[PDB]
Length: 367
Ligand SMILES: CCC[C@H](O)[C@H](NC[C@@H]1Cc2cccc(c2)CCCCc2cc(cc(N(CCC)S(C)(=O)=O)c2)C(=O)N1)C(=O)NCC(C)C
Image (cartoon, rainbow, N blue to C red; front, side):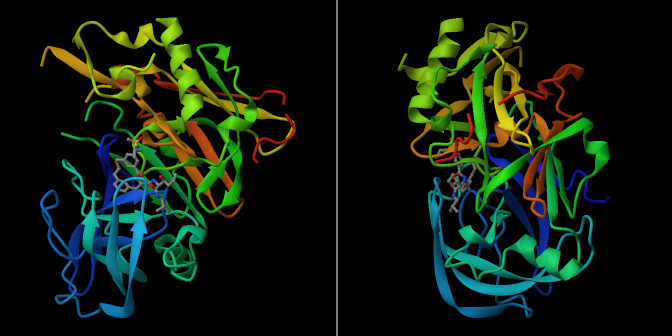
């Protein structure tokens, strides 16, 4: 469809989509975020962003009468909850009527180097603010364009933070954006896009951790989270395993980069990490494997990288760094998350991620 390469960005600061808003249309760039389910834009100005949304100059704007605050793991913001007409040049050409928040105060939400100026929440209504009545952007498109309740991403920016992008397909799958077969894990709770992680295998070496700690609170697919966050002590074990292949110092914690003359690639010094996820039938499972290329992030005859895994307190987040390796399908209608190899996820024309299945299975791992 026309929806291919409608995204643009990297894993460092995010992937965004060009949207037209209001009457007449204001050209905004909207971060795509499967970790939240609120659609919001910058209603007043700010320094890292270069364009904002002017509600005065949109006659099709209407205010709903209340403000709302949204707090994320990174930053927060408060905005008027209006609604307005939105048009996505790529794929639709039609105007849609959607709730929208215009942000008039943001704390640590607009970071340096962002090229976007709003956020689009593609998660379930459960996470909407101030409640579940605010109808998500994507829920409106389903109900208004009688498209299927399905979207699918492809992020090809597996290089280094001009930035090549990817595709956001609304209404289903674009089969030129993957190769091979698709493995579907079910959605364990239709709030975040929570899935059931069965195992972690660090370079052939299963983790000693209990299966239950991987889904300690939730294990989610979050296009808004840059990295692969892990529950703290899961991270620790993971860190030791990777370290053992070579505790509590700067690179792992991200306060230092490691730099190599451009010729040497450190990736072979690291191990492939495998996430084993449950297939749609209990008995089976499968694994998505990101190689060192994805988690050793490069941020010219030398290159300077960072360890691309950070520790979380409650949740395990499959951020965009893990999602860049694959084509991700968010099938909300059959409550599943689909994974497949992504052709554009190929540095030097070699595969940077792999997907393999099936496998034999604890009884339940979600507490
Ligand atoms: C799982 C719970 C929610 C999930 O976290 C979800 N993640 C998506 C958010 C969205 C967001 C907001 C502001 C700025 C960004 C994006 C920029 C992306 C790049 C930096 C980044 C972002 C997040 C998160 C990180 N990282 C964690 C550090 C705080 S990191 C460095 O990649 O590991 C970096 C993050 O939380 N993005 C969330 O935060 N909140 C959802 C509720 C409000 C509904």
